[PDB]
Amino acid sequence: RGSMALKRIQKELSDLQRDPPAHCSAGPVGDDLFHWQATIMGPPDSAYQGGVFFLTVHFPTDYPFKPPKIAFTTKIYHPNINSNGSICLDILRSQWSPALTVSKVLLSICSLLCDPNPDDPLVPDIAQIYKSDKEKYNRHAREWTQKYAM
């Protein structure tokens, strides 16, 4: 990182809360500005509402040029996310730009939770249930939300 990605982080933080998401939160864990942690609240009108999800954000030494290493610590019944919390979002590498911020990624996942990507499964069966029948999908998620995110 040198001192640049590092300042990039500071900027990412000082600006992160100038206008706080009132729903999500992220920041450096302990004395490591390259090791962050975040918390997302299930959008009130989504299957994951009322739940608290923990995320671990790892900043690449070459940031902001490369995307941040983030994982879902809290169990979540989502087709684009698996048993180890790995998240597969387009902007995480396939369509990522230095411009985008960690904040951005938050809202991205926030909407991703609401509107998932079925043909892009990380877990085929949960992606198949969504597509074939969301009515059932939107329950499992609730069951998991209060059993893993309460």
Image (spheres, rainbow, N blue to C red):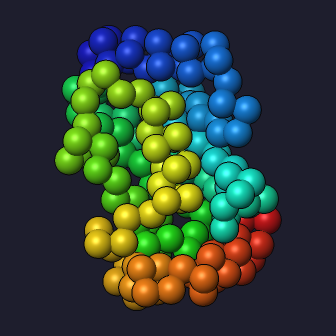
Residue at the (65%, 39%) spot, across then down: 24
Report whether 86 appears left or right of 39: left
Q: Position of residue 16 (x, y in %)?
A: 56, 21
Q: Position of residue 100 (x, y in %)?
A: 36, 27
Residue at the (47%, 79%) spot, across then down: 130
Report whether 58 appears left or right of 113: left
The number of callouts visible is 0
Report whether 86 appears left or right of 4: right
Vertically, is 80 above or below 126? above
Q: Nearer the viewer, residue 37 or 23?
A: 23
Visible residue check, residue 35 = no
Report whether 99 appears left or right of 78: left
Vertically, is 47 above or below 2? below
Residue at the (55%, 74%) spot, across then down: 77
Q: Nearer the viewer, residue 132 or 82?
A: 132
Residue at the (29%, 68%) spot, across then down: 120
Quadrant showing the N terminus:
top left
Q: Position of residue 66 (x, y in %)?
A: 23, 33
Toward which corner of the image does residue 63 lie, by quadrant?
A: top left
Q: Nearer the viewer, residue 35 or 42?
A: 42
Visible residue check, residue 73 = yes
Q: Position of residue 95 (x, y in %)?
A: 23, 42
Quadrant showing the C terminus:
bottom right
Vertically, is 101 above or below 57? above
